[PDB]
Amino acid sequence: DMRPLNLAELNDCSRYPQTPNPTFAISPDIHPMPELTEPIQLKNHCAVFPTVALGESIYVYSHQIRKTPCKSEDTTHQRVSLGRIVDRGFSGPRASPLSTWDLQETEFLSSCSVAASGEIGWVLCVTTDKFTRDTVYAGPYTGLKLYKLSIRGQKEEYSITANNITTDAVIIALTLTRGSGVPKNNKLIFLGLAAVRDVDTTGVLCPTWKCDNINNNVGSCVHSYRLTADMNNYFMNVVVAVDVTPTGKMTASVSLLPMSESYIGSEGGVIDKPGGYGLMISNKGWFARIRYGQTDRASPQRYEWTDYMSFETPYYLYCSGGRICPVSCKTWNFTVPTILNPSGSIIIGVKAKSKTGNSASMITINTPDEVIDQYEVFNDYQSIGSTITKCFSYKRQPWCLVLLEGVLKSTGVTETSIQTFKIFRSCVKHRTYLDSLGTRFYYTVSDNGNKTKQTYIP
Ligand SMILES: *[C@@H]1O[C@H](CO)[C@@H](O[C@@H]2O[C@H](CO)[C@@H](O)[C@H](O)[C@H]2NC(C)=O)[C@H](O)[C@H]1NC(C)=O
Ligand SMILES: *[C@@H]1O[C@H](CO)[C@@H](O)[C@H](O)[C@H]1NC(C)=O
Ligand SMILES: [Mg+2]
Figure 1 (cartoon, protein in one colour):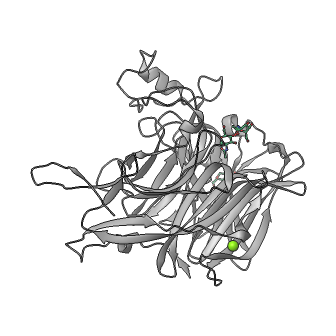
Figure 2: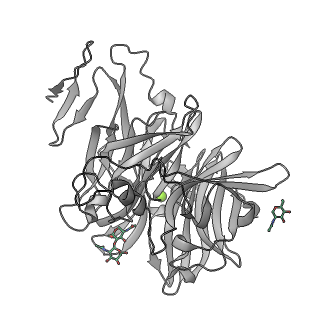
């Protein structure tokens, strides 16, 4: 019933030269997945840091489990479940859980993320001897552990010590983001967050316009990567690549995303695309827009980056706005979109939500500079602290799910939940967009190199 979304097919409007532009709309109905939805706390245990991956028919879903008052040091195991996304006669898909595992060892599995390839599930975890509130910022960590899972049961476990991981930076702490990894070539590629020393600052992304009460923009930009009193500890994103050889030997590498390519280490995920992969990031910091970096064979550079000025992060729920300028305020909320075309020039995601200020969640479909469609949703939540959107083919139609963490209004209970909604694809003469007041418009491009708007009257 469920397969990966074929992005090339979804965007193939080429047989329609008179309506050649792909576009997308959000279907008005949100559908529950009750078997994948649960409170954070239940009967002396907490289930935190949810992460999900989708494969051919299967999903892989995982939470870190803690006992007692649910501090970091109370972590007891990693719960992982594998099931299928199926039609059970409802208007939206449902989960059919097949296997649940409780993964554990003497060391803590301090941070884990999941991936799926075909009907095989993978769980990659950072291991540590001690796990505290400070592990994410200062470590230490001892290595990685990789679990291979199928419907029947666990197949294999692999591990590698930190000293055997090839790295291009001085890495003091390593955490995996909640977004899934992706199988690419014979490897698994995951996004990580690392505490790093001795980094190069050349080319740090930083505006050159005037910023309030700042003469040295560059220094403010560099300083804003730091989360602790240690002046030589920068919080940055890394790409974690793991391989298992036929002999069953695990190798791993961790590659820094330099300051010239990305902002402070933030949540995100790896995106599969034809011919490569991308890194979708929901910045914690002052550059408060979604960014997407993808492999670029043509360009000698590794990653080509897209800034979605149209798609704000949750930054402004809790930090002051204004001209985009380096400041210290950060949010830990995050919203990871996914791509709807091969190049990621069209993305879809779900906004977060505060309990104040007329804050509302929205599903939004965007290009870098425009909003294609948006829909206010999740009035049943008083707040939403994180979202991860993933899309797939179900019943031969484009569908998406969102994994979110938030507080339900009716009960005040914090929950992790997964819900689904259908997408509508069409091929159009002129793609329409929404202006800041919600009026729909399109551009009547001209051959001399000009564009003018026009209002869509329904
Ligand atoms: C999203 O951000 C909010 C605001 O910073 C976080 O809520 C704060 O942090 C904890 C809640 O766990 C409390 O100590 C504070 O009182 C909260 N403030 C408010 C206004 O609620 C929230 O935890 C974040 N959620 C995620 C998933 O990042
Ligand atoms: C690192 O890898 C080498 C080569 O496989 C192996 O001999 C060595 O035991 C590993 N080190 C640790 C600490 O496991
Ligand atoms: Mg369900």
